[PDB]
Amino acid sequence: MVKQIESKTAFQEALDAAGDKLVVVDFSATWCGPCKMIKPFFHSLSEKYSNVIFLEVDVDDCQDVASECEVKSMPTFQFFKKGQKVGEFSGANKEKLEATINELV
């Protein structure tokens, strides 16, 4: 249920294939503690919201994607519809993550 992204090609393809659907992107790093604390919850959301698309991008694997998306904070959650960014926040705030999904879906 979470799409593990390992190139720019794959990121762009995912935003395409989403169609109309909200896409939620978790930008993480392996050194990021809060990223680990929220990982299981992010995966829970992908099973709960089966009609929303969830992507995982490790910023060191996909540096071009990280750079082009202007990621600063670890973690960062960005939200897309039809390829357009429609939301963003940083930090591992579970309640805010779910609430944002419900606002944008």
Image: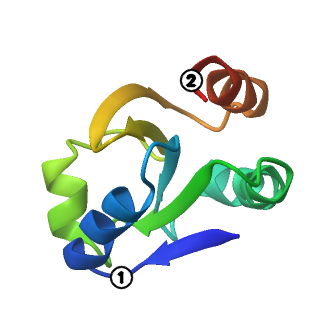
Please name the residue that numbered disc 2 is placed on.
104
Whole-Å distance between the Cαs marked 2 and 1?
Answer: 26 Å
Residue 94 versus residue 61 in the image, above or below: above
Residue under the point 15% across and 54% down = 67
Q: Give the residue type that dot 1 points to.
A: Glu
Element under disc 1: loop
Residue under the point 32% across and 79% down = 61
Please tell me which of labels 2 and 1 falls first in the chain: 1
Element under disc 2: helix
Please name the residue that numbered disc 1 is placed on.
6
* Residue 50 placement, left or right of 91: right
**Residue 85 in picture, x, y percent from top left:** 31, 33
Residue at the farthest top position? 103
- Which quadrant is home to the N terminus? bottom right
Observer-nearest residue: 19 or 54? 19
- Which quadrant is home to the C terminus? top right
Residue under the point 34% across and 65% down = 59
Q: Residues within 10 Å of mark 1 (few under 14, many from 20)?
A: some
* Residue 63 placement, left or right of 45: left
**Residue 66 in picture, x, y percent from top left:** 25, 57
Residue 50 versus residue 72 in the image, above or below: below
**Residue 99 in picture, x, y percent from top left:** 72, 21
Residue 8 versus residue 6 in the image, above or below: above
Residue at the farthest front position? 19
* Residue 21 placement, left or right of 59: right
Q: From the viewer's perspective, is the residue at label 2 or at label 1 nearer?
A: 2
Q: Which mark is residue 40?
A: none
Residue under the point 43% across and 65% down = 57
Q: Residues within 10 Å of mark 2 (few under 14, many from 20)?
A: some
Q: Give the residue type that dot 2 points to.
A: Leu
Coloring applied to the structure: rainbow
